[PDB]
Length: 27
Ligand SMILES: [Zn+2]
Image (cartoon, rainbow, N blue to C red; front, side, top):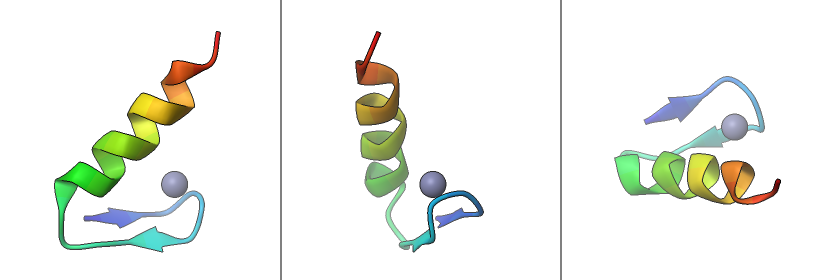
């Protein structure tokens, strides 16, 4: 939906999911 952090705001939870996935992707 809306991300306060990195200026991101999409109406698709996949986007955030990708953010968390990629962000959490790194050790
Ligand atoms: Zn963010």
